[PDB]
Length: 298
Length: 115
Ligand SMILES: Nc1ncnc2c1ncn2[C@@H]1O[C@H](CSc2ccc(Cl)c(C(=O)O)c2)[C@@H](O)[C@H]1O
Ligand SMILES: [Zn+2]
Ligand SMILES: [Zn+2]
Image (cartoon, rainbow over all chains, first blue to last red; front, top):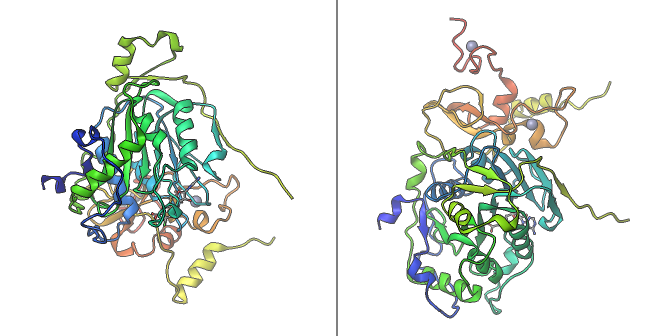
């Protein structure tokens, strides 16, 4: 596999076009581990490879870019993924992160609490989520679409993602949501991306590239998750840390992508085509204001 | 007049043989950077490692106030370069050392302003 020198593997288009039934995920390389560079944590390696893959897509990168990162804490009380995002994003990018549990972070602002308590006045150019509930991994009951934070994420995308913006949302065999797959059809392009360092896990990042705010294609999320598991079940991915050793072209290119305010009636097919090419962001350019709802009781 | 002196407490803990603070966030980078102490992106040279700044700050990590009137942190949101020989204890290194104000390197670990 030439794939071992890539940052990871994206779900091939033909697999997206199938109509598979959902099966249990049984990875050939389950339990194997990549050899990480000395002293480098899995979460730093994983986010580095995610960002290396996002470098290959037509991301909109405006001045004063706005990025929000959900699930950014660790059981060590630090934010390794936020540290990689801050390394990757252009200097001056506004980066906000959040987690249920307290942690210390390099983000410009951090909100502690359930993601459902997070509200923002502004729209965002990029949404990253690593949220995961390990209780979903119950091999003994039916693997149905999950709600919880996925319900929040779906609404947050529809209400607070700028047109032209993108997302990368962690899923696993058991941690997934049908509506989130359906929402992937509201972007110009989408994939499920597996990092080469964590290829022994059913984890992937569901990536929606350039948001259009309306269905471009109709996706059945139950079918699409079955398609994803079928791909993983029949395509073993060789664990690899190779791409971690060449960081010379890591930083996200500062593209100066135009930001315009438009009301829904002026989004014509010419605007939709600029959005689809990563050439336009549609949102206000006012002040970024966030808050966390606090439940007050005795 | 009472103030908790966490810096002294950590130094005394280290000198008594305590294990340094762990889980400082080490970054992947080229190791062909400027080598300056505290930077907006990782700048480790061949002799350094680069770390996320908040994770190397004693006050950030211990959840205590920063020792200045404004409570501002010099590390959070930045990257700190640590000599590889000292990278087992980034918090202790940043606590014990000083940045040269003209060249931006660590005094005694890159600053050549006095030779
Ligand atoms: N509804 C919600 N709102 C806000 N934050 C949320 C959230 N749900 C989860 N998180 C947060 O996401 C982060 C990553 S999840 C995780 C946790 C432990 C392990 Cl051990 C693993 C693993 O197996 O790798 C993965 C966690 O820090 C969690 O606190
Ligand atoms: Zn601090
Ligand atoms: Zn000097």
